[PDB]
Length: 80
Image (tube, rainbow, N blue to C red):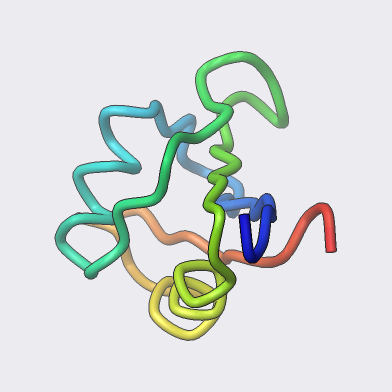
């Protein structure tokens, strides 16, 4: 729509899953459309999408190098 973006949500010790990352994201105030998770990286990173950069910039300032129930995630723009 007004936008289309994709972000990475990742760090190193955590093979996170879509259920896990949406759980945290709702904790944190994200929602998004969806995320590319479970497939491969070091083992398991997510990569979210939304039609409006509000949600992108949010996580880039809400989830960037945050501790995730005892793991951590670093998050960033990945198609922009």
